[PDB]
Image (cartoon, coloured by chain):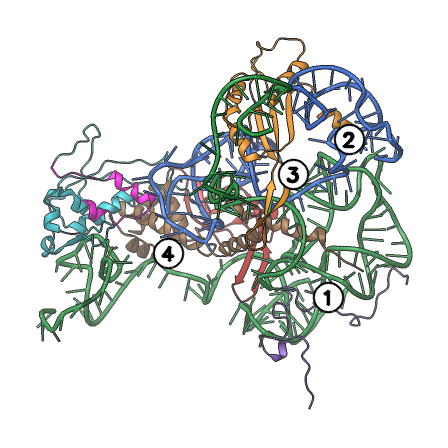
Chain colours: A purple, B brown, C red, D cyan, E orange, F green, G blue
Amino acid sequence: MNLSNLQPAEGSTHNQNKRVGRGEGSGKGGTAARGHKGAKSRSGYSKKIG
Amino acid sequence: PRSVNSVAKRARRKKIMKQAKGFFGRRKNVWTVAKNAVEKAMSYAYRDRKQNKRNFRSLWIQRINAGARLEGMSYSQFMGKVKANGIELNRKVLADLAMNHPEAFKAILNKVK
Amino acid sequence: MYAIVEIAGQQFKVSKDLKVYVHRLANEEGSKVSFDKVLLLDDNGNVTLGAPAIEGASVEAKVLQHLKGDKVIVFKKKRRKGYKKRNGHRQYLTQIVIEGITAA
Amino acid sequence: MDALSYKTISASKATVTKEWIVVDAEGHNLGRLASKVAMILRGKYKPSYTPHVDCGDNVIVINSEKINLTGTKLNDKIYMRHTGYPGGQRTLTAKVLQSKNPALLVEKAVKGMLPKNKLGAELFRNLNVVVGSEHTHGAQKPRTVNLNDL
Amino acid sequence: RKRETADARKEANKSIAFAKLNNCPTSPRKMRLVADLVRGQKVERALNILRFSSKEASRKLEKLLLSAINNWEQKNSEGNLEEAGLFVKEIRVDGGMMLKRLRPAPQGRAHRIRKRSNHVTIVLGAIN
RNA sequence: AUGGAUAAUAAUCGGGCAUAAGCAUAUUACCGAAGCUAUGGAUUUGCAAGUUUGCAAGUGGUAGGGGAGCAUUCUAACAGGGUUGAAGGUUUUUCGUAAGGAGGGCUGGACUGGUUAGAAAAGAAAAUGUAGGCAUAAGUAACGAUAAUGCGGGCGAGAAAC
RNA sequence: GAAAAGAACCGUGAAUAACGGAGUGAAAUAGAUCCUGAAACCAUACGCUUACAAGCGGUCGGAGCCCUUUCGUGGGGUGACG
C-alpha cells in the first residue's frame, strides 16, 4: 500500500542472522562446524575433486 | 557501516554481576571471577531444590517419631496403623500437629490405636 | 475452630479469617468457592478426626486475585562439553480469603 | 514474596527447655547405654526437634565406674592416641584406661555418636560423667530417668 | 536539574572548616602511618605528635593542621579558639599521579620505578 | 569356627561400638531417587474446530543437522520526543522461555528515536593474543669496590653530604 | 569556556608548594592533568557479625540485630547454627 507497509510473500525471507562461531547457545559454536582436529578442519581446506 | 556494541556490552555484564552481591574477595567486582561464580551459584540453586523436598520430609518424620514415642509407640507402627485406617494426612500436617497441638496428635493416636 | 483442607493438591491449616496462597484456580476474581475436602476439624474443644472428605464439613473462601510468584532461574550446565541453558520460571498462584468453615 | 503461606515452625533458643536428666549406669553395656545417652543429648524425644539448634537435655551419668563390657573387651580393647611425632602412636587398653579416671570410657563412648560439628562439640559440654555415685550440681533438682522406658 | 541551583545547594562549606594538601611528593602508605596517630585526637595533642614524630612525613603535615586551624578561625570570626576545643574529625590520605622512570638492571634489561604522590585532606569539627 | 610369618609416615567393619547391632530361613511395618502418581504451567509433532482450543505420543545430550528470535551501526517511508532537560554514567521497580523491553530518582548539558522493509566492519572468557591503566610479591631486594671520618663557625625556614 | 572574562586582593605557610576565602560565569565538583567522565586499584565514616575453630568460599534452611513500609503469610542489610 505505502512505503511503510511493505510486506513480501510468506516464505520468501529467511533468518539472515545465522553466523557460525558465535558462542554456545546458537548451535554452531566453539569448534564452529568442522568437528575436532584434522585436515578438514584447517583454514584453507579445499576438496581435491579427482 | 561500523557497528560497535559498546554500551550493551557492559550493560549485559552489569546485570550478571549485580547478583554476585555479598561474595568474598574479588568474586563481586572482577568480571571474569564473578561470572564464573554466578553460573556455579545458579547450578547449585537448580539442585538443592530437589533436596529441599526430601530434607523437610526427614524433619517431619523425625518429629512424628518423637511425638509418637511419647505414647509408647514407634514411627513405623504408627504410620502403618494410620495408613491402614483411612486417614490420609501428610507428614507435614502430622508433624505440625505433633509440635503445636499435642492434644490433637494424641487424639489421632488413640483413634488409630 | 481450625480445620485442614486439601484445596488444589495440598493440605493447609485453614483458619476462620486466613489468607492462603494456592495454585491457579479456574475461578474468576472476586468469586465464592467451596471446598468439601476437610480431613480434620477442631472447634477448640474436640477434634472430629475421621475418614477423608468428611460429609458435612466444607470450607468457604473468596478469590482475591490471580498472581505469579517470584521468578526462579533454572540453569543447567555440563562442564567441558559447552552445553548450558538458563530459563526463567514463575508460578501461577491464586490468593483466597477464608470466610467460614461449615461443620456438619 | 513468601508464597508458601504454611511453614514448618522451627524451635529457637528462646523456646527450648533443657532438663537435667540423671542416668544410672550400674547394669548396662557400654555402647547400649551410650546410644541412648547420645540420643537424649542430641534431643530427639521431643516433638520440637530442630537439627540446627542445641535442643535436648543435660545427662548426668552417676555410675560410670560400674559399667561393664560383654566379651573380653576389657582386656582386648585398644585406644590409639597418636601424638604427631615420628613413631608416636600410643596404644592403651580398656583395663588400663579405667584404672585412671574410669569416666573416660563413657566419655569416649558418647563422643563419637555425636554430629562431629560445632553443634556436637557444644553438645558434649552438656554431658556430665561422674565416677562416683553422687554428682556436684546440687541446686538444680535433677530427675532420674531409666533408659528402659524409651 | 538546574546546575546553578545544585551548586548553590552544595555550597554548604561556609560552616565546615577543612584543609587540603595536593601533589605532595611522598608515598601514601608512609603518610597513612602518621595519619592514624592523629585521627581523632585533640587539635593540640595532634600538633605535639606531629612535631615530635620521627618521620619525614610529618614536617609538612604539621603545618596543614595549622592551615586548617587558621581556616576555622577565618570562618568562625566571632569567637575565640580555645573555648571551642577543636579536634581532628576526619583525615584521609589518598593517592596521586605518579611519575615513571627506568633503572637499568643487569644483562641489558630495564625495570620500572614509580615515584608516587599523595593527597591529604583534613576536617576539624568542634566540641563546643 | 581354629593354626597355617609379615613391610617399611598412625591405624581401621567408614567410625562409635555391638556377644547381638554377627550368621542361616521365614513374616510384617517402615525409610528410601530427578522412577511412578497428585496440582499448576510451558513447548514439539499428528489428528479436528476455527482463524487459539481439544485429544494422543513425546520433551538427557557431545560431534553434527533444522526452526523461531534479541541487541548493535546505518539507510527508505509514515509518525514523534528534547535546555519545562537528549545521548552517556549510577541506583531502583516491573514485564518476557531467554537474548532483552519499559518506567522513576541522582550526575550530565545536546541530540535522539517508534512501526514496516533493507544492509552488515553485527555480540569474547581463554589464542604462553595486542595497547593503555592499575595491583601482588612489599615498604621486601637494593641504594653500584671494606680509602674514613670528627668538631667549630657562615648563608639559610630547613645542614651527617654545601 | 559562548566569549579568557585564565582567579585583582586577603589569610596560613619560609615560599609566586598547596589550600581556604573574595571576584568572572549558567556552572570552578568547567581552574589550564580543565566537556561527560565508568572498571580495575587505593582509602574514610556508618549498620550487622567475627579471637575452640579446618577445605572451589557457594546453595538450601535458619534465629538474633539494624532501616523502610500501601502495614505486610511486604521490602532491604548483616547474619550465630545445620
Using the image as rendered, state which of residue B94 and residue C78 is in the foreground: C78
Host chain of mark 1: A
The amino acid sitting under disc 3 is Met
Of marks 2 and 1, the one in the foreground: 2
Q: Are marks 1 and 3 on the same chain?
A: no
Position of the N terminus of chain D by quadrant: top right
Of marks 4 and 1, the one in the foreground: 1
Q: As displayed, is residue D77 above or below residue E3? A: below
User: In x, y percent, where is residue F3?
Assistant: 9, 70
Q: Is residue B71 visible?
A: no
Residue under label 1: A17
Of marks 3 and 2, the one in the foreground: 3
Using the image as rendered, state which of residue F161 and residue E104 is in the foreground: F161
Q: Are marks 2 and 4 on the same chain?
A: no
Residue under label 4: B86
* Contact? badges 1 and 3 (CB < 8 Å): no
Q: Calculate the distance from the C-alpha at mark 2 to the C-alpha at mark 4.
A: 77 Å
Sooner in the amino-acid sequence: mark 3 or mark 2: 2
Taking the image as shown, residue D103 lies to the left or right of residue G12, namely left
Of marks 2 and 4, the one in the foreground: 2
Residue under label 2: E3
* Contact? badges 3 and 2 (CB < 8 Å): no
Q: Calculate the distance from the C-alpha at mark 3 to the C-alpha at mark 2.
A: 29 Å
Using the image as rendered, state which of residue E42 and residue F35 is in the foreground: E42
Q: Residues within 10 Å of mark 1 (few under 14, many from 20)?
A: few
Residue under label 3: E97
Of marks 3 and 4, the one in the foreground: 3
